[PDB]
Image (cartoon, coloured by chain):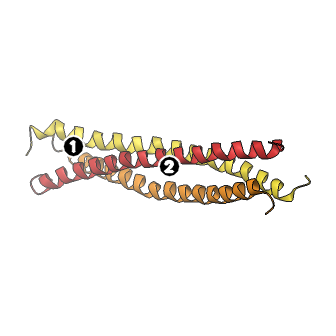
Chain colours: A red, B orange, C yellow
Amino acid sequence: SSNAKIDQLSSDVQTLNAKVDQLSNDVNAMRSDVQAAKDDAARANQRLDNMATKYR
Amino acid sequence: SSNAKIDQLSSDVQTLNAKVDQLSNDVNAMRSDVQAAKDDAARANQRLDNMATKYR
Amino acid sequence: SSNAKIDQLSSDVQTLNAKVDQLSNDVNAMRSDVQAAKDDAARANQRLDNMATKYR
């Protein structure tokens, strides 16, 4: 356009929009990993609970 | 204003500011979940340590 | 510059670029913690597997 500054800003904003959307995906993807960890930990403790009344 | 392009950029920047602030909350919230997982895992291993000198 | 609005937008975009880059670091840093949790959980369950054929 007739304004180089505006053109650069527009480009940077488009890039930011994408970077933000990507970080959103990254965060959401990490959620499944956190739940996986949390679930495996509960699984370990559950197993221990299942034998704690038998072994001390 | 007299510049439609600037108005659109301003709006997009305001939205980005909010989206970034939100992602910040999401990340911080996930921290408590990660620590919860990490703590429950250590708890399982601690329990195992407490009986490992008794059972092999 | 001759446009206060553009100057403010430019500043805000620079700040956003930094905030986004930082969130990227925060997310990446959290990854090592999630893996740590996941690994310690697997470690607990592995230990349990190692004695499950001996104790029920």
Where is mark 2, residue-wise?
A24
In this rendered view, identify the residue nearer to me: C39 or B15. Answer: B15
The residue at the point 64 percent across, 42 percent down is A15
In this rendered view, identify the residue nearer to me: A20 or A42. Answer: A20
**Would you identify the image quadrant in which residue C25 lies?**
top right
Measure the C-alpha gap from mark 2 to mark 1: 43 Å
Q: Amino acid at mark 2?
A: Ser
Mark 2 near mark 1, Cβ–Cβ under 8 Å?
A: no
Chain name for mark 1: B
- Circle 2 Cα neighbour tier, 10 Å, few/some/many (<14 / 14–19 / ≥20): some
Q: Nearer the viewer, mark 2 or mark 1?
A: 2
Q: Amino acid at mark 1?
A: Ala
- Determine the secondary structure under disc 2: helix
Position of the N terminus of chain A, as image quadrant, is top right
- Circle 1 Cα neighbour tier, 10 Å, few/some/many (<14 / 14–19 / ≥20): few
Q: Residue furthest right?
A: C2
In this rendered view, identify the residue nearer to me: B22 or A21. Answer: A21
* B23 lies above or below C34: below
Q: Residue furthest bottom?
A: B1
Q: Is residue B51 left or right of residue A10?
A: left
Where is mark 1, residue-wise?
B52
Label disc, if present, on residue C23 of the rendered structure:
none
Q: Position of residue C50 (x, y in %)?
A: 17, 36
Q: Position of residue C51 (x, y in %)?
A: 15, 39
